[PDB]
Image (tube, rainbow, N blue to C red; front, side, top):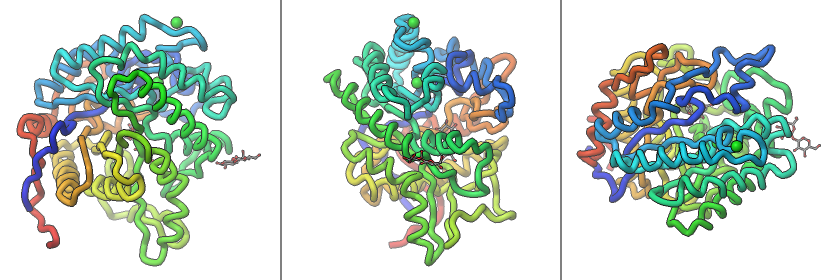
Length: 401
Ligand SMILES: OC[C@H]1O[C@@H](O[C@@H]2[C@@H](O)[C@H](O)[C@@H](CO)O[C@@H]2O)[C@H](O)[C@@H](O)[C@@H]1O
Ligand SMILES: OC[C@H]1O[C@@H](O[C@@H]2[C@@H](O)[C@H](O)[C@@H](CO)O[C@H]2O)[C@H](O)[C@@H](O)[C@@H]1O
Ligand SMILES: [Cl-]
Ligand SMILES: [Cl-]
């Protein structure tokens, strides 16, 4: 019904991840998987957006559009290309990104880990191997020159619940996803990423640089059909809630939401045949983030919430505007209800490599895969303008009360 001004210092921006935009990330586990014999990965990442060279243009564009914040990742595979050999070259590359954000009036949120790992880290047995926790923490300590000045927010591990899910697949040797919901996570990896996270928090806080640290959650918005509450709770806990519980002592927690999955007495039910879908196959559900935020609050307590990824894969930008109008309304609504939300970062700043395909275009900013030309979409112009306005618009539908 009425507009909700940004809280003071509210993050307003977009998010990317190194492997999805940078191009030539050739020391990652993913680079190997993309080219392995028998890979199921539909297409290779290759040059992606070449943000390795073109992040200056990325950030010029974001700032010009009126965004005030940029979440990007720094890449362990580059920083530690072989075990024990830290690249000062790549550390400086990443420090230049932080400084470059600041010089363009963008507050940088730094993700230290976004799914990919060094191939050597995978080859030695991944998150569940002996020493994996110490290895991650050492990498985190080594990022100190990148994050010790000018960075207010660090994300340790992006969506550890997706890590645990995929480890569950790899352990069973499963290649396909169920028609709804998520594969049983590997509880071993669950434990390992949680211990890795706490150790990373210690490392960042040890810098005594005031950094707010936490991690981000792939919120599924599991909804119980009436009667199926207990099944829904059991299903969601290892997939989501256990990672939110591990964040209860953190300085902030990231909410990443896109769609919803209904759960019946037998478990996850797929979207109806006739309901609107996005280019990811997911049900179009603009109000997801609303439920994601509220569920996250219920579980995590009073840890500040930030939306660190939210959007839609679509070829129709006016449908993206629709999606954000509903998502922003849910953010406003949660704020007005008194949730402590301190930022909104859209997924994604650019069209990017969506873990195996380039067809699932999530970008505010269009990318030509041949020339690397950036073209802001209209959604980008509108959302960006809110960085100056600093007020969340509402949809024209009525609230209760
Ligand atoms: O791969 C099957 C199953 O493994 C699960 O992990 C188990 C682990 O918790 C247990 O300690 C040991 C005991 O030998 O067995 C398994 O490794 C994992 O959580 C599931 O995702 C997998 O489906
Ligand atoms: O897919 C768009 C972006 O979203 C993230 O990962 C999502 C996750 O949020 C969601 O729960 C699952 C559904 O099974 O899909 C993943 O792709 C990542 O932050 C981004 O890398 C990803 O591109
Ligand atoms: Cl090196
Ligand atoms: Cl990384």
